[PDB]
Amino acid sequence: AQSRTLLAGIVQQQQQLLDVVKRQQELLRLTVWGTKNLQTRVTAIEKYLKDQAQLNAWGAAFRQVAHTTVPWPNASLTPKWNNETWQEWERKVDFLEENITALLEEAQIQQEKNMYELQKLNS
Amino acid sequence: AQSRTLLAGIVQQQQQLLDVVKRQQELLRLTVWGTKNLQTRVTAIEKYLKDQAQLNAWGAAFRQVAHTTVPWPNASLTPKWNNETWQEWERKVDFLEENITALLEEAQIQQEKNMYELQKLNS
Amino acid sequence: AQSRTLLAGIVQQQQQLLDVVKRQQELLRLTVWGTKNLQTRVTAIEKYLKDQAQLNAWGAAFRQVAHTTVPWPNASLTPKWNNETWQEWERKVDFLEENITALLEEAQIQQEKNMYELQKLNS
């Protein structure tokens, strides 16, 4: 008279939900790659911006033996403020990924134990 | 003597969790739009950077009938390496979205079946 | 003869899944900060690009009492089209965060009620 079939669906449903949660974790990682990839493109642009500062005046002296070069800074490079703050951002993600993996591990162990107990009821 | 009320809460709870998971999928899509939107802005900047290369020296020749134009490349355009890698990134998201939709469909069908079975117990 | 132990695992499992979902919400917020942070860097670049337009020709006139300054626009600033569309993007996230918080609140209240009912069965 036990409703094992109803429990099997409920237990099975939890497994389905757990799988979808895992898919979100992999999807989230793909998004992180896009953001980081954009930064790499930004660094390439900074190099080119520095070149523009080098460009100042060509042939602006055909009656003098001198050339005016004005390589004024162009791209503001972040040495410590963004790096320290960005590492903190990455660090928070690392703790969340480690905490989520722990919870997923317990769920998998608990999920299998719940199904195992169900078989013992009528097996 | 069956604990249908406890099961109704458990079954109902799974429905609530399923709804929240769906909300994350829509929220994830909004984040993807922001990343892609930034790239469109980056392309506009590349056009302007090319213009800076065109700027070289104006009036740098008032004793000669010539003008020095130095349009040296400025923005490094990605033709195949980033596109092929980016398509792979988008492709992975497409498979994950299709797999998540399949799991959600099964959960909805299974979720309704679990509630339907519960009514048959006392209906 | 009630399978409270099986229910305790199922009820406990839902709590574990709820916790992981909350972790995704915090992880999603960290990703939003990275995207917004990139835009701040982009604004700094726009200021520098304007400076490049100012750079035109230095000393390109050693036989005339005039200087040619050509500060042609460089960074295309978005005043209304991107802001209005971006606010809509942020607005959608705000409604999703508010809706997810509501669902989480109901789950927590319902989750505790389900455990409370279980104790009454044998307490």
Image (cartoon, coloured by chain):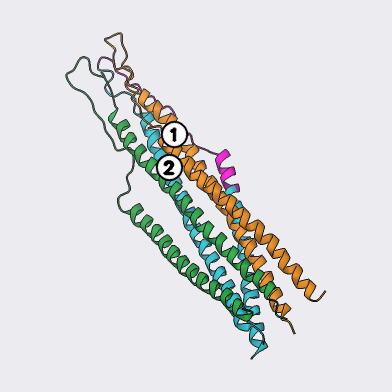
Chain colours: A green, B orange, C cyan
**Residue A29 left/right relative to B94:** left
Secondary element at tag 1: helix
Which quadrant of the figure has residue A50? top left
Q: Which residue is label 1 attached to?
A: B45
| Quarter of the image with the N terminus of chain C in it | bottom right
Q: Which residue is label 2 attached to?
A: C42
Q: Which residue type carries mark 1?
A: Ile
Q: Position of residue B52 (x, y in %)?
A: 37, 27
Look at the image and say whether residue A58 sits in the magenta stretch: no
A121 shown above or below C49: below
| Helix, strand or loop for the magenta stretch, by majority | loop
**Residue B62 left/right relative to C18:** left
- Range covered by the magenta-colored residues: C63-88
Subunit under mark 2: C
Question: What is the tally of numbered marks visible in this picture?
Answer: 2
Q: Position of residue A55 (x, y in %)?
A: 29, 27
Q: Which residue type carries mark 2?
A: Val
Q: Position of residue C30 (x, y in %)?
A: 47, 57
Subunit under mark 1: B
Can residue C80 be seen from the camera position used here?
Answer: no
Q: Residues within 10 Å of mark 1 (few under 14, many from 20)?
A: many
A115 shown above or below B75: below
A48 shown above or below A21: above
Q: Position of residue A17 (x, y in %)?
A: 59, 64
Look at the image and say whether residue C71 sits in the magenta stretch: yes
B92 shown above or below C14: above
Q: CA distance from mark 2 to mark 1?
A: 10 Å
